[PDB]
Length: 287
Ligand SMILES: [Mg+2]
Image (cartoon, rainbow, N blue to C red):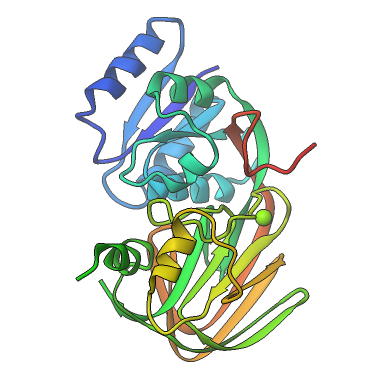
């Protein structure tokens, strides 16, 4: 079936992508390519996708583009809403990796056009911003050892990071104390390979919570985020909602977009969006 590929500003000179798209066009497939320039554009092209009667709107880009498209799709009122497909055309591609999208773009394209579509959750913060992958929160200022800088810059989108007090409540969950990193996940992975929520499933109606207590980012935290480390200094929960509050501003990075304040209500939007996913998809619950 026909698709509309929503491409980023950083994709218009990807020759392999062009080659792949072009090779699939000359196989009988209808594939519209639209390029975004500013926010609001994905929305505009999502609705043009509708007018065409298209079956998949394909986010070609980073976790940001996927979130722009996803957010636009869930806002659609009506009957014939396109499934979400995903091309891994970002720098980090955390969500795409974690849901098993193939690196081979012809394959990823084909998945995105002809895969099975399944309803997945999204999440919303403060009845406003939505996210499909991960919300990471910490206390710091907005943006020697590279392991550590990578976390503060890439994962947290900050220049500084310090622990501070907060309280967090959710179903079966109540905690107060100093936290260095808060991970609230629909997906499992953020900031280029950091495993914030190893146990996340994207269609269980449930957000994973992990609170990393600390002092600073130590080999502890770098270790525990890369591969798997089983660690007592990590507090875990699972809830359809989490409330977070703090005497000083916490900064949440929601699929790459910052938000600050003393109070956050984060809540699952159950089965909000159909996404084209491989059958083995590690983040879908067993059936
Ligand atoms: Mg879940």
